[PDB]
Amino acid sequence: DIIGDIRMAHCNVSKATWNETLGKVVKQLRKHFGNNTIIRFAQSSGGD
Amino acid sequence: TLQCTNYAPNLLSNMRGELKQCSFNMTTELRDKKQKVYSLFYRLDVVQ
Amino acid sequence: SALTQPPSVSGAPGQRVTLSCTGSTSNIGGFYVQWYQQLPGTAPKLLIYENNKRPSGLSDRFSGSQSGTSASLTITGLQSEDEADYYCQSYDNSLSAQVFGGGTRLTVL
Amino acid sequence: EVQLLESGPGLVKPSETLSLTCAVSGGSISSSNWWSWIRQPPGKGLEWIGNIGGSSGNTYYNPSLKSRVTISKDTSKNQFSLKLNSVTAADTAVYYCARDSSGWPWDNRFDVWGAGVLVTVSSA
Ligand SMILES: *[C@@H]1O[C@H](CO)[C@@H](O[C@@H]2O[C@H](CO)[C@@H](O[C@@H]3O[C@H](CO)[C@@H](O)[C@H](O)[C@@H]3O)[C@H](O)[C@H]2NC(C)=O)[C@H](O)[C@H]1NC(C)=O
Ligand SMILES: *[C@@H]1O[C@H](CO)[C@@H](O)[C@H](O)[C@H]1NC(C)=O
Ligand SMILES: *[C@@H]1O[C@H](CO)[C@@H](O)[C@H](O)[C@H]1NC(C)=O
Image 1 (tube, chains in turn purple, yellow, brown, cyan):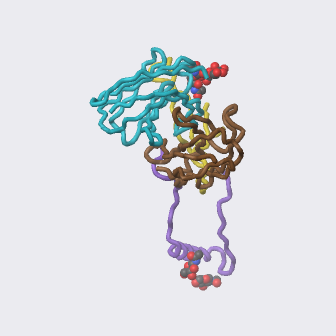
Image 2 (cartoon, each protein chain N blue to C red):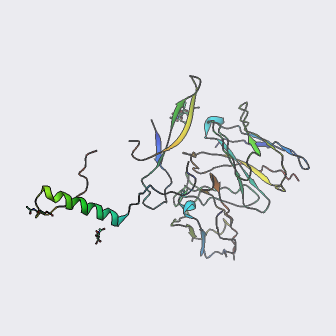
Image 3 (cartoon, rainbow over the protein chains, first blue to last red):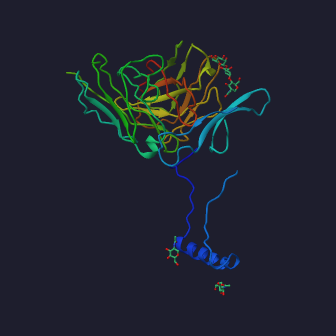
C-alpha cells in the first residue's frame, strides 16, 4: 500500500538540445530525399 | 476470479483510472484451507 | 489530523446549520467518508451509505451532502426531536491511518 | 442484527497488564470481516485501534501505539479479546467493540457498523 501522495511517472528532457539534434539529423537526411521537399513528423500509428 | 474496484476516488487529478484495488482467494501452506489477501494493480494489468 | 468544525455552531429549529470538515489532498482523496453519529451516554451510532446517499434499509429520510476538497453537510428540515451530536471519520495517508478528529455540539431554541 | 456482545471488566489501575473481553451470540466469528476496537477518553473525540483478522490472517495496528498493544482471538465462542501490556499513559478511557458489515475494508474501509453497548473501564 501507498505511503505518501499519489502522482505518476513522468520524464523530463531538455527542449533546446533536442531541437538542435533533430534539426541536425533532418538536415543530414535531406540528402536522401531531394534538397527541396517538405518533411513532417507524426506520432505513432497504433497497434498494440 | 477477482473482486475488484477502482482504488481511492475523489482524487480528481490526471491520476484517476490508475491503480485499481482487487481481492481474491488463495490456497494456504496446507492444502485444504483457504486464505484471503488483498492487493493493488494497474489498470493495464487486469481485464474484466 | 482533521479540521472538523469546533462546536460553536448554533443549532435551532430553523435548520440553518452546516457541517464542514477541512481535508488535505491525501485526506479527501482517500474516499468518501461519513455522517453517522448520535447522542452521548451511548456509543453514538447512526449509519450513512458512506456519502451523500441513503443508508442501509432506512435510518432517516433526511440528509444530503457533497464533497469537493471538503466534507460538507448543510442540513435543513425540522428534526429538532433528533437533537443529537456528530463526529467524523476518515482515512488519511499517515502510515495507514484510519483516523479523524471529529466532534459536534449543536442546540435548540 | 442478532447480537449479544458483552464485556468482562478488569481494574488494572497502578499496574500494567490490561486484558478485557467481549463475545457475541449472533452469527459467528467468520460471518463478517472482523471485529474492531475504538477508545475514547471521557470528553475527547475518539482513538481508533487497528484491527485483527478473524475471517482473515492479517492484523493491523495503530501508530503511537507500536510494539505496545497485542491483539488476538480465541475462536471458542466469539472471543476476540485483548492482552495489551505495559499501560503507562493517563488514558483512563472508555472502549467499544465493533462489527464490519463491510465490502472491502481492506485497503482502508467500508463503513464500520459497530453496535456495542457500554464497554467501560475507568482504570487509573
Ligand atoms: C474464498 O473461499 C472461502 C471459502 O469458501 C469463501 O468463504 C465463503 O464463501 C461463500 C461464497 O463465496 C459464502 O457463501 C455465501 O454466503 C451468503 C451469506 O448469506 C449466502 O447467501 C450465499 O448463498 C453463500 O452461502 C460464505 O459466506 C463464505 N464463508 C463461509 C464461512 O462459508 C470466500 O467468500 C471466498 N472469497 C472470495 C470468493 O473472494
Ligand atoms: C529549435 O531550435 C532553434 C535553435 O536553433 C530555436 O530557434 C527554436 O525555438 C527551437 N524550437 C523548438 C520547438 O525547440
Ligand atoms: C543539396 O544540398 C547540399 C547541402 O549542403 C549541397 O551540398 C548539395 O550540393 C546539394 N545538391 C543538389 C543536387 O542540389
